[PDB]
Amino acid sequence: MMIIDCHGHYTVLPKAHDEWREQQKAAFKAYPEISDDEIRETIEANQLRLIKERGADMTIFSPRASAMAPHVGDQSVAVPWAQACNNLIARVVDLFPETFAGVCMLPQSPEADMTSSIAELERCVNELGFIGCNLNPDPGGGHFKHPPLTDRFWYPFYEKMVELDVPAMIHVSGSCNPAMHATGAYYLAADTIAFMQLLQGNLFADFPTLRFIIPHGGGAVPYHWGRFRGLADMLKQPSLDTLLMNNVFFDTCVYHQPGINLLADVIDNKNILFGSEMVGAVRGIDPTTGHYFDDTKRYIDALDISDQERHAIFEGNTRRVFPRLDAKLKARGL
Amino acid sequence: IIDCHGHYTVLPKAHDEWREQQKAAFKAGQPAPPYPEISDDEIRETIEANQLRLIKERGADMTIFSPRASAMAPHVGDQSVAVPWAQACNNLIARVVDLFPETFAGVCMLPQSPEADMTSSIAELERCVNELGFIGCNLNPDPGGGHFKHPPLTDRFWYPFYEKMVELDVPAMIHVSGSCNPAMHATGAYYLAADTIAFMQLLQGNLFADFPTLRFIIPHGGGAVPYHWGRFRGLADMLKQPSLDTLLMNNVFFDTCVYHQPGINLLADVIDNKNILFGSEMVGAVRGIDPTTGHYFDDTKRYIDALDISDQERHAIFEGNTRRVFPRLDAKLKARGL
Ligand SMILES: O=C(O)C[C@@](O)(CC(=O)C(=O)O)C(=O)O
Ligand SMILES: O=C(O)C[C@@](O)(CC(=O)C(=O)O)C(=O)O
Ligand SMILES: [Zn+2]
Ligand SMILES: [Zn+2]
């Protein structure tokens, strides 16, 4: 079985990229040339080394999430940034095509509809060979002032996803809200809110093939699985298994064994996708284990499950959720 | 067996009716109508049919009891509404407490509104604690109702209120109310996000250096926190902050309002025993049976019961921890020779 990591961002970048970013905002408040060897550098010393150390084969790789910051920022700012962030990913893929597959950030901004986003999706899937995207449920950056995912506002975009046969990870970005830390508060809240928004309507009755990944082990959701099943009856809604769990998936970016145990316990096997978000939110060693918080393969490994279960989690669920990756690997005879 | 989280949810019908007339008069710039005469037995009926019925069946002894949280609705509208509403809501709890003083202890809602400082909440805290003998309050981190637009709990906007809490030796349950944000359901999303956000606000600063004996309960088993304990421990280092045990966990406690065994399993596993306070939030967020067990979602005693813990651990969860976090309740119980 292949070990595919479904959650990863290019987090250690050539300086020039981020400096241009700041000057963009400064020329707004009022692009650099990067070499192959610079990118080879940033990736060899970081993700490529850890993949090797940790026994992984592939990582589904997108732009640093907290740097998307669509709230800057109108459509004239977001488009070029989203294009350049995604162009960097396609070069990382180019350079390491057996190791990275591309997921794209969208040029969302607080005031725009999904037109440009539909355009970058097509450019990335159709011309850059990308396999999925990251979808930001709150481009404003901290106050959740966008319409819930059940809103028709988002529909033309899902029509594209469904045309291209590509899933989306629900993923907010950096916070412009002093009351809200990003990787420790905003990210987990959005995971939960996004799940609950879907439990309120019935989106997948309209798009039965639409697939979402809710990162970080679904936020608070599996921990409160009892609460959510119970709210389905409170709201007169269909059960979570029929309403959501053919279309909603959770990664295993939960950085400790007990959390990983609960995830495997209450959530069905087909809904769990191996992911680790390495070199990201939490980079240090765990003082209680001697192993890195984000070396999540270790937690899956220590589970007491069958090969059939381990395989789905490490390879098969992800190839199901990402059809365009499954076909890329089938073509390589894998 | 002391339930640290319960709300007066099934209420005399006149109270609910007044509230609607109150908001209706405010929206039309008119005087609010007189608050209705509610009979002792009107209150008795509601408690006897619901909370008391369930306490007995479940073998609890008492509940720390507060107004219905989703009804607090501080985003409706200004102080001229918030103050009379809160006073009225807390008076009912005080009446419930008078009629069943062996069973319920009072915790108060605050007259928080989006445009006000905490001056009026300090006063109501004083009223209920000094005059009405309540043992705590519910502190709302986002009176704005769904957009998290207030300052974090670390901000000195909250400091004068914190001083009053220390003076009276009372804890606060961090708790939001209804949502005005269509992107955010109250009990399934807002409440949980609120818990998680409150915890990270604390992780970022060091409020308990300034107030060594300030005490917060983060409800619903700590939101996403225990499930993500490793992420939070790691985040402390990413932030070059002290360890959670020292930074937060002598001042922060979680309830057991987790509505399935596996969740209660994780909570006991990862959180120190002294930080866990039995609660159930009965007749509230989730009121039906769990098709997979044949038992009620919120009958949380059943989950603690199934834990392979010692008699001492159980005692702390059901009785000991709560008595430490609410000294006034502790003192009241001692005075009764318990
Ligand atoms: O930027 C970081 O260092 C952290 C991080 O990679 C974290 C992140 O994306 C996640 O927690 O899923 C981010 O982009 O925000
Ligand atoms: O409104 C209700 O009945 C639900 C509820 O009881 C829920 C609640 O308070 C909680 O889950 O903590 C409330 O008061 O908000
Ligand atoms: Zn991420
Ligand atoms: Zn509550």
Image (cartoon, coloured by chain):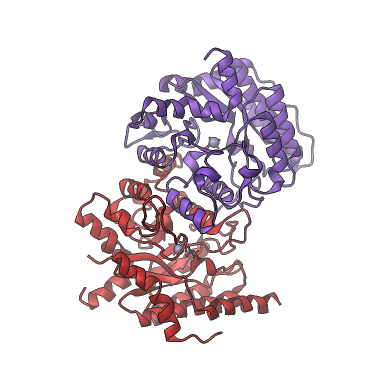
Chain colours: A red, B purple
Q: Position of residue B142 (x, y in %)?
A: 63, 46
> Is A47 in front, or is B142?
A47
Q: Confirm whether residue B228 shows in the render.
A: no
Q: Position of residue B89 (x, y in %)?
A: 65, 29
> Is A231 in front, or is A226?
A226
Q: Residue at x 40, y 56 (%)?
A: A293
User: Against A329, is B325 above or below?
Assistant: above
Q: Residue at x 35, y 40 (%)?
A: B262
Q: Residue at x 51, y 21 (%)?
A: B62
In the figure, residue B138 lies in which quadrant?
Answer: top right
User: Against A212, is B185 above or below?
Assistant: above
In this rendering, position of residue A217 left or right of residue A176: left
User: Against B181, is B96 above or below?
Assistant: above
In the figure, residue B99 lies in which quadrant?
Answer: top right
Q: Position of residue B236 (x, y in %)?
A: 51, 53
In this rendering, position of residue A211 left or right of residue B94: left
In this rendering, position of residue B240 left or right of residue B214: left
Q: Confirm whether residue A48 shows in the render.
A: yes
User: Against B67, is A156 above or below?
Assistant: below
Q: Residue at x 38, y 68 (%)?
A: A162
Q: Position of residue A138 (x, y in %)?
A: 55, 61
Number of dots carrying numbers: 0
> Is B78 in front, or is B139?
B139
Which residue lies most toward the top here?
B337
